[PDB]
Amino acid sequence: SEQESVKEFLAKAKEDFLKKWENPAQNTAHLDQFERIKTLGTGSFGRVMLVKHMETGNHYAMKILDKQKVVKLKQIEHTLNEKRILQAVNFPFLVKLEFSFKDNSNLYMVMEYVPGGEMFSHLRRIGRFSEPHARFYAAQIVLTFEYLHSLDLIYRDLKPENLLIDQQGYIQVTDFGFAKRVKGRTWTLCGTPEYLAPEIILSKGYNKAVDWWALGVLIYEMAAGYPPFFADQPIQIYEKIVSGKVRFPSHFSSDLKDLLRNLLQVDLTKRFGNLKNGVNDIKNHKWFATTDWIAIYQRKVEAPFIPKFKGPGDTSNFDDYEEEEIRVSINEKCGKEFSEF
Amino acid sequence: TTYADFIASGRTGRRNAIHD
Ligand SMILES: COc1ccc(O)c(C(=O)c2ccc(C(=O)N[C@@H]3CCCNC[C@H]3NC(=O)c3ccncc3)cc2)c1F
Image (cartoon, rainbow over all chains, first blue to last red; front, side):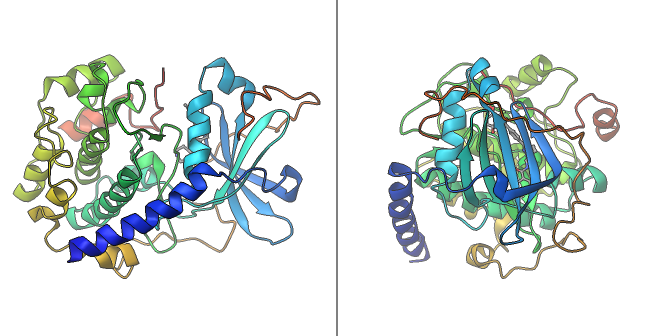
């Protein structure tokens, strides 16, 4: 019946998502409505900046992407997926898209600012999380993938760099640049080397199960302080991943090792998340026995770690990046390519 | 230790995605 209650929530959620999926919001703001303060991160085609909405005084995080660069690297479809998916989803552990627009030069997405910083920063500094602390975060991702996959979405870039910590210590998943709505298999070689499932590396055509593999990698990295497969160059990482050989730190609880053995299963018919029982194989595993899944969804559970921040606009949980002036050309670049954005 | 090998590795910073 708990299982039925989740089944009901998902059907409702799917109806909401499809309305926005089929009729996406367009052009709901303008650049000169925002004051640009500081860069919080970068990516291949641009950056995310803290901004202040001038008429409300609210702070947001604005992704700016350069259209020409996107087109040069043939990443049009993926950037169009990012915005289309992000505007349609609604979940407590997904970052909220507030506005989007474009001009002659750039694409813009204005999201909720998540001031606690990236999980990556905290994990590197502290070293590793204790199993209860990792479990807390893992549970939020389990539910988030349960949500996303019911919508036929695959996320494909789970890593601590894309998990922001909010003021209450919960996760907000960001950076949907490889998210894709797909009913069957797909083939793009994409993602972050350390987190790539074997079937992606092997050019096999793959599905949602790549997200469950990636969750395995994440939980390991959270609890070990390093990922299961690492080396100085990508090619050596790929070799380790396809070999199907994982060593666990001596301090891992036997329940944690057993989970990871099922998530880091090279064999897709054996991988937790890809079985007839679906996500329930994961939620019912012994490592999660103390997890109250609904309390997590509702956010009544007490976060093991709450980031400090002196007020809105505070960026102290973020690294410093070099700033660059945003130039907007007088001539429209790549109009047809981005017409739906 | 594996921790020490990770820390001396070239991949302890932010990791970029690859694409097609
Ligand atoms: C195929 O390649 C793609 C596809 C889609 C894309 O959007 C991009 C990007 O160019 C791109 C640009 C900027 C970023 C970025 O700056 N992201 C930051 C830093 C990287 C790690 N993820 C965290 C992210 N931070 C936030 O999204 C954020 C959100 C809300 N509050 C604070 C931070 C990421 C990707 C891209 F390169």
